[PDB]
Amino acid sequence: LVHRILPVAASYSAVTRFIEEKSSFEYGQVNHALAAAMRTLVKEHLILVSQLEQLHRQGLLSLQKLWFYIQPAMRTMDILASLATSVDKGECLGGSTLSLLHDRSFSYTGDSQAQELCLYLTKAASAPY
Amino acid sequence: PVLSFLYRWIYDGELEDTYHEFFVASDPTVKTDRLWHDKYTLRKSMIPSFMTMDQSRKVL
Image 1 (cartoon, chains in turn yellow, green):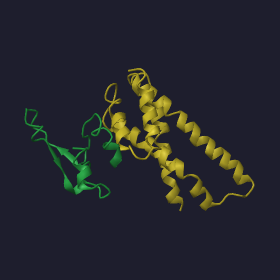
Image 2 (image 1 turned 90 degrees about the vertical axis):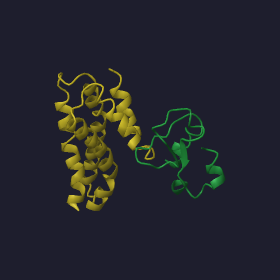
Image 3 (image 1 turned 135 degrees about the vertical axis):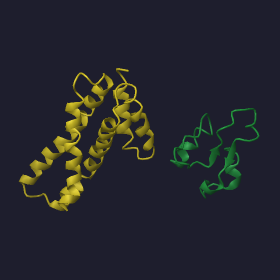
């Protein structure tokens, strides 16, 4: 069961590294605002651990309940891991990093949860350009 | 998603399907005067069964 929950942890260790590294000045000006708006969604992820933590004090938390509680974060944090690895895999800086995002914004058109996230990252990233 | 593609090629639009899905499967290679005659096969295999053949042949 713990292995089943570990991917969100693996999909977290690999976003925060992206937000710091691609926050250097060298990476254009759209690669900047991409990481900086991927910061509103690490706020969400920390607070859910915190409020869940205050629930565990009263002994009213179970491993099964946790596994059920963290489903949404298994997904939002995971979409941010593909976007990060794909910007890294093919060096993307400038107009290329504003195309890869317009590609994912179609790779989802029916989820209506994992689009609003991609479609916010795109409207945010394309204000400098 | 099926009815997503069918709200632009039914009003103003183009067939975007990286992987073939929407029934209209247009032919590239020909931008000449031969399209109101020959550029748009109705791929019969991807007409969803909730659409009769007679409805699927007005969208195209």
